[PDB]
Length: 207
Length: 207
Ligand SMILES: OC[C@H]1O[C@@H](O[C@H]2[C@H](O)[C@@H](O)[C@H](O[C@@H]3[C@@H](O)[C@H](O[C@H]4[C@H](O)[C@@H](O)[C@H](O[C@H]5[C@H](O)[C@@H](O)[C@H](O[C@H]6[C@H](O)[C@@H](O)[C@H](O[C@@H]7[C@@H](O)[C@H](O[C@H]8[C@H](O)[C@@H](O)[C@H](O)O[C@@H]8CO)O[C@H](CO)[C@H]7O)O[C@@H]6CO)O[C@@H]5CO)O[C@@H]4CO)O[C@H](CO)[C@H]3O)O[C@@H]2CO)[C@H](O)[C@@H](O)[C@@H]1O
View: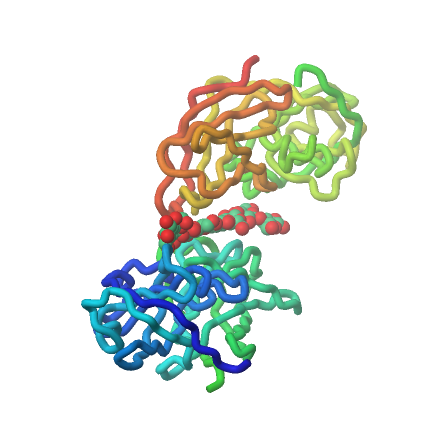
């Protein structure tokens, strides 16, 4: 059915503010964040499906919302590793591990997607990340010669393809609800950029 | 390689000195070279098997030896597209096409292999080309955790693999006669190299 909660346990950690597997840096220190177990992270057989999602997390002392910035490698199904500023709002940190119920919620954000084009990217091979997205990005495609080509999502929260073609890149993104939106990204470099770079986008998933 | 024989036709072209498919630049402008039909290029099911090979070619007026630098995309079985300085030695330039016989021969070179590490190569993905080899290179393997891993030869005359591991790279090369030599290459970088570079090798195929 429509919007189920997930039972699990929360622990806490100070990692994930920097060097998180989803390459979402910089994370401001006042942000409530979490790492997420692999089974839940990879919903639908899509690697990093929940990367950059937001979760409402309910514990014994209340509820709070966290930004998913990292993998919780040894986490069981249902398990989250929150930042302590988030954890304290829903449980006593003396307890170390707490019972929780969580679910994906609409991101508390404004504006459009922002894209990050990974170092190494070119017309030959590219890795494109979506940031500032209101719901998990389950799918990304690009058009080439009138056909839409699926992009595999990677563990490091970018969508990848090869031989994408020349000129501007028409892309389309699908969320966890199945809503599809469409955008354009400027032509990829002749050859691999030494640095990742940012492209502010011009669409957002519907409310 | 010791013995071999092909019958076909040759034409001639000015291409292949620069920007040839096999990424063998720079080629001296007065070197004797040829482009080669796809069927014979991809001998034994190896893409670009004969890239960087040397052929002895016989026409009506004599024989000469040529360096294979490019693909002859439209050539039929046995067909070659020679540089005009090579065509001149074995045929009448006033003909647009000639009967030829040819065979893979020992490279008229001295010294050991040279490797070219393609731009963007790293421990995660690498494309390695062998240069200055006496016979066609049919196979390249590298060692990883005590096991030998085969690298796919690409159309662009490099061998490719992924997750090659850290540290210096033990490789082994097999020619078209089935001769095998082994060597070591310096470690690959942690991120895609910004520029292609060459590295001196320390072995050569036997005479
Ligand atoms: O999280 C906790 C967990 O951690 C675990 O460890 C993790 C660790 O935490 C992670 O950091 C790490 O994950 C990531 C890692 O996987 C990642 O790997 C990437 C890397 O970043 C990239 O840089 C690299 O990029 C290369 C591509 O892979 C490669 O495929 C691409 O290929 C291109 C070439 O670039 C291009 O030059 C080439 O050549 C062209 C030809 O295409 C062309 O052909 C055409 C002809 O011209 C034309 O005539 C004909 O008609 O058409 C032809 C086309 O069909 O020819 C021209 C010349 O003519 C050539 O120039 O073409 C290729 C096209 O595909 O190049 C890329 C260059 O960058 O990719 C790799 C992946 O492969 O790195 C990141 C770093 O941030 C890392 O995060 O993983 C580890 C391990 O899991 C722990 O294990 C665990 O314990 C913890 O719990």
